[PDB]
Length: 258
Ligand SMILES: O=C(CCCCCCC(=O)Nc1ccccc1)NO
Ligand SMILES: [Zn+2]
Image 1 (cartoon, helix red, strand yellow):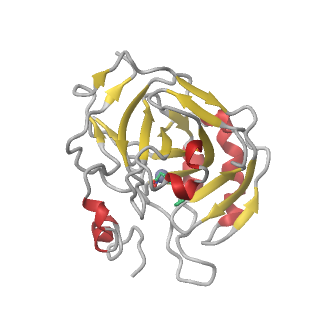
Image 2 (cartoon, protein in one colour):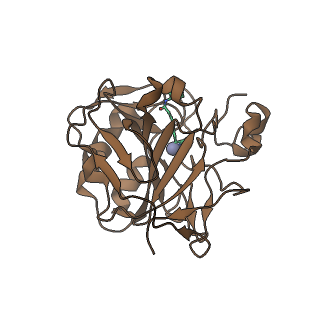
Image 3 (tube, rainbow, N blue to C red):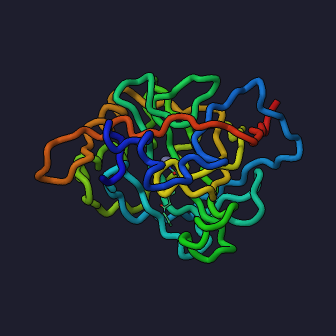
């Protein structure tokens, strides 16, 4: 039926409704650190998040997401491999049922406990619906989470998850500063790819940060208490909402660092 992450509707089934699932620039991929090419032409990333305005947090039945006001150039991503200004729209996570799985991208086959996606769209296309139809429409910053010490900047998110336990629930979520989610270093890998959920459009410049952030076991445990189901339905824990690595095909992964 409708897509999801289960045995009968999971990633291996998506191609029947979304044939681009077997396309030429699908995501995620395994990053082979010894075959990635250092590209000295790549610029440092410019992340300008000081004026970000968060609006709401919502359980969309596949993940939870925090949405931002993107009606002006308030929180923007520029530089790196990008040409032009990309506005922050939302962030969300992918995570596992166990600490040794949950990320979408992998690094030399290593899986992390979760992966944070900060989604931005290219302002030259005017709105995000137009941007997803363009090969350079979106830029997604991917950040790995490892289990270790707690991340204090994540705690405001963890503490509101009880309010959005089931599909379709939303809550006001103002004055959240996404700078608290970034690692110290902005070194990155980049490659052209796709959304990792339907409709799997091939519109994404991926920027995957090398340095993971550390979150505590108690913080990630709280993600695993969310539900895929809506209020009143059989309880199905929201875990393992990650797509497996896809073939690299004719693409090169570039590194900003040696
Ligand atoms: O695929 C990803 C990362 C990119 C997610 C892109 C979602 C875009 C969004 O929130 N709004 C939108 C979706 C479809 C069409 C237009 C806007 N993770 O699974
Ligand atoms: Zn994602």
